Length: 585
Image (cartoon, one colour):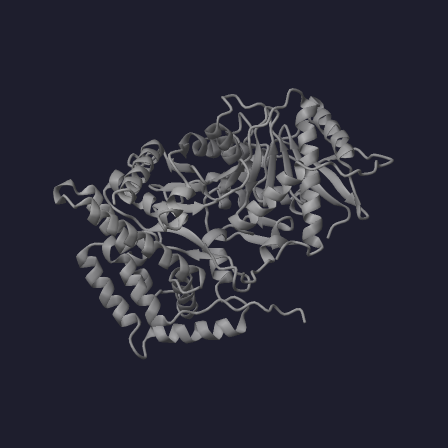
């Protein structure tokens, strides 16, 4: 029947994870600290010890659940994070710059994009999405039926059938309900255009302008939860929130950008709207997909990460965009046409105080982000593959060298590995800061050692081999992050006081990803980007093409050590160095 024929996420052998763990951290902590961690781990995983006890409960959990880490992961990775979603968590995809001579051009694009969204959702709901190895498809079903509720300490991801179906249109910080489906009736691209025009007009009505409530969703999670609590007191607000929570997605008709339309600037608008003064309030972050269609041509989609990952987000986005290049299939006029409904809000002195706070908070995020879009154009996948190297592993090694040559040390690095092979599979982590990576970067940067180029090349290839090996380990569910997480939380269930194993500074440091990365390859002229995950870290999202590689680098201005410009430069030098290395003889 209806039971998944997929395999369950595998539980690695306790000793395998512990050995890999120590191997992963040895070169990332002091000798003294390592010696202490060795003893701690030794005691934790000893015969008849706590480790084996937790391992048995995990095995029991594996049997009783579809995926033993789903709950732990969802909370640890997103729902527990208190940071505001903009920049800190919600990635953004930037489409190619568009040209909208008039407002109707902008609206036509929006109408077409909405049409593309509905066609995709139709395939989705009809289970007509193109299913090598079979993969879990749950994420697809969370694209338009998800909503991330804020909480005092832990957020809640709500999994939603309405009639009719609708989308929320944001214009001038005002939100409107736009019914797009009514009795399997699906609005024509033409009716959408007409409806959007009505929206733009009402949105321009001063006597009807309401407070920019969307600004509240850009604040810290606990701060937004508190403000939402004030909101829910009123029956009108409850209704409006409900409509937002049950929409298919948002469509933000953003005002003019103020700066030049470069790749870096357009991305900034998609990341945080440029603050309240710009389009910062013309949003709603709890909702998974917010498609932006700016008047000046800046378009893209802001994604809330909790419900699904990069692969699914891109497949959906590229399907839309491609759909937009296709002949418009003739769709029938609606008679009569109802007028989109503006969502009303019952403001208060409190809410007014929350808006002011959110505005300042969001402003700190804006001025604090150091973002750059660097396009490496010397070579791409073509050259790398000719070196018998995986493009991803090659670039991951380049990032390690770039970080080392700039800051003189390696750091716990994050790189997602998809585990969709297994039921409800999300991801896991690939630890790119390998021992081999260290030997390679050291040989390259230690002038005084005078390591022969021939030797550096050997170290280079061994580092890439190690990268690829860890990658394969992670994707087959044999890595260490999810495993340790489950062991940690199962212990917590036994006693709030965690085992020394997880209180060890080595463990705490191993999960502070100073270098958070991800490869988001696209076939379209679009790119993905996101912020750092720790105050003193970077955000590195790359898109490798046949002859070039796009790099989106983020870091915080607050940290004097990091510099997106310098890191982008170090990446260039690292890729050049590696090219020359592969070109000796």
